[PDB]
Image: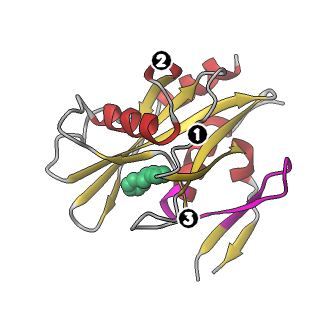
Amino acid sequence: SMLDDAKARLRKYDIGGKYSHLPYNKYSVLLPLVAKEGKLHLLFTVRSEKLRRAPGEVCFPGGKRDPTDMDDAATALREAQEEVGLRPHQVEVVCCLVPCLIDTDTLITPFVGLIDHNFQAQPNPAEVKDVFLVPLAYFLHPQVHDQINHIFEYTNPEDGVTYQIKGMTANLAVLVAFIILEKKPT
Ligand SMILES: O=C(Cc1ccccc1)Nc1ccon1
């Protein structure tokens, strides 16, 4: 099936806990996969305008590890619950992808999660201005704008709203799209 095929592809790229004990300032992100209308989508947040760093930017749910977290996956799930109301029973964490090194002292670990079809986002307005879906196949043929570095513009056909996706967020979306959709029969 579509979902069994996606999980099987994703498991081949799982690094597991290999880099998780290293002495960095630690953050985790959740790459949330949603199945609608017979296709896979990624769920994104728009950060509240009130926030100190990167107000109004498109991001994945996530944040800083705290002492309560049993592991890096737990960080991603705690932050996702706080930000968009995603409960643990509504997500299956399938794997841990390549971590992102930044600032010389910081390691950001991404986890891909399959999201339950009965989940409905409840944006917490102190942290998140908006939540939206992009079809995973978009990241194979994105509408690119050069700012000089590459920015994706996605327009939601439901309402005509345009979102800008860039940086680590755009990079990870492309990675997930390649892993799941490369070399598939029609
Ligand atoms: O902050 C994140 C993810 C993140 C954290 C740290 C480093 C890179 C990415 N997601 C949010 C926060 C509010 O709305 N979305």
What residue is pinned by disc 1?
Answer: 179
On screen, residue 92 above or below 184: above
**Residue 55 or residue 106, whichever sits in front:** 55
Image point (67%, 40%), residue name: 182
Q: Position of residue 153 (x, y in %)?
A: 72, 64
Give the structural element (helix, strand or loop) at label 3. loop
Q: Is residue 113 magenta?
A: no
In whole angstroms, how far apart are the C-alphas of marks 1 and 2?
25 Å
Residue under label 3, please give it: 56
* Quarter that holds the C terminus: top right
Q: Residue visible at 79% across and 26% down?
A: 38
Q: Residues within 10 Å of mark 2 (few under 14, many from 20)?
A: few
Chain-order first, disc 1 or disc 2: 2
Q: Residue 62: in sight, yes or no? A: yes
Number of marks in picture: 3
Which of pointers 1 and 2 indicates the residue nearer the eye?
2
The residue beneath circle 2 is: 89
Q: Residue at 58% across / 77% down in the picture?
A: 149
Q: Is residue 59 left or right of residue 150?
A: left
- Magenta-highlighted residues: 152-169
In the image, is 175 to the left or to the right of 88? Answer: right
Q: CA distance from mark 1 to mark 3?
A: 29 Å
Q: Position of residue 70 (x, y in %)?
A: 23, 28
Is 22 located above or below residue 120 in the figure?
below
* Residue 150 percent across, percent down from the top left: 62, 72
Q: Residue furthest bottom?
A: 148
Q: Secondary structure at mark 2?
A: helix
**Position in image of residue 8 (x %, y %):** 55, 23
- Three-letter amino acid code at the position of disc 1: Ile
Residue 127 in the figure: left or right of residue 42: left
Q: Residue at x 55, y 24 (%)?
A: 7
